[PDB]
Image (cartoon, rainbow, N blue to C red; front, side, top):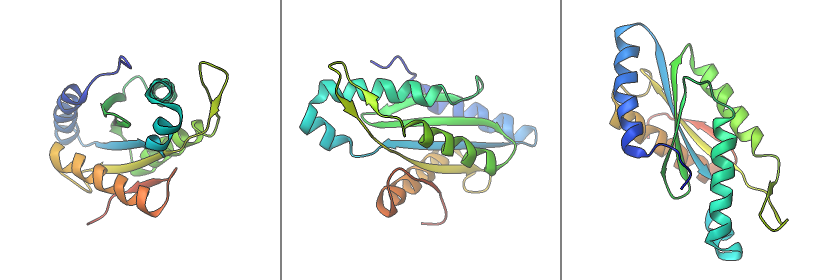
Length: 161
């Protein structure tokens, strides 16, 4: 266990954060992070190593967020981050850049072995992209798929797909 809040919890914070944002004129963002080439790592190193990587990734994500932001594991190799309140989309991209830059440093395994991985991020914005939690999540999900598709270790802002 990574000790990070789960999906259910994340969806809750989102609903309320979305309200707060709408009530008072503010912006919020949902970022989706997918560890690059996770499967290959498992096959070659095993699931035990995969976990150690997830844990490390969890810390590297949290260590780059404001105490106001939220980090939760959607499951397996994917994480979901809440950026609220946001002053603009530029900030959301700024934080994503930082998250991807923190992964540039190799991950030291329990037996001295090193593992270098990348983070693919899909950024969905409110209220530009979506007006509700579901859609905002779906948008961050799809934008995170295309990124994996176009390039990995990259961030991608949703647009009509």
